[PDB]
Length: 257
Ligand SMILES: C[C@]12CC[C@H]3[C@@H](CC=C4C[C@@H](OS(N)(=O)=O)CC[C@@]43C)[C@@H]1CC[C@@H]2C=O
Ligand SMILES: [Zn+2]
Image (cartoon, rainbow, N blue to C red; front, side, top):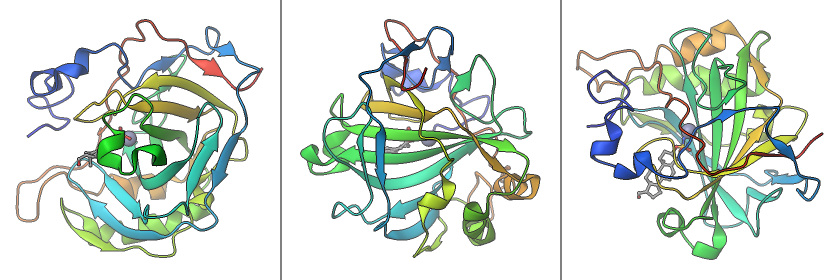
């Protein structure tokens, strides 16, 4: 029922999910001059060498690549985190044009798109339990700008024609998400939420300062996806981003000076 349109979009979500107006909602604008350098923050540990991708899916709000999270094969640790977070899936948010698409903004700057790698805390045993906990999830956010192609993204772009409409899925084995990472793991971090329903306040956000560059041809392929099911009027899958929410009583911390 919820979506990104005039009648069902982010301004409507609070009616089915009242936590939409809560104290720790995401995304937010990252004010770079107000974010505090925290020399206590550790380097982020990204261990994706044994990642096992399974499927790529159009879920009617994005597309996601899903991983085997039944063992510690692809894990996020350190940075602001206590303990071990398993990679469940990655997905993107993007715009109708290059000047919008990111969920987080930097000094009010919007990027063409934003990549989210979703991880859950192994101390809670499964992701359904983890979303009920204030430290249940860690989402690694990476900005996309349009320029040079990202070679590591091309395998994803080339299969999108096979999952054009909602619920369509395909085999997507042996995909290496290390090919989506920028050089630097310098980050901002703050306590927040899922950015779609159910908007659960379970997320430690880790947003990388360095964007990756993707080509216009790569992002054009995102914009050919459809929100609609096969045979329905349909409706290009574009502008699937929630706008920045009030920071309220929260501090954004920087890992870097
Ligand atoms: C599957 C669930 C509902 C959907 C939840 C998932 C946890 C995290 C994300 C990531 C989020 O996007 S974002 N932008 O916040 O990272 C989109 C929603 C989604 C897929 C839940 C785990 C349990 C729950 C129902 O069984
Ligand atoms: Zn997301």
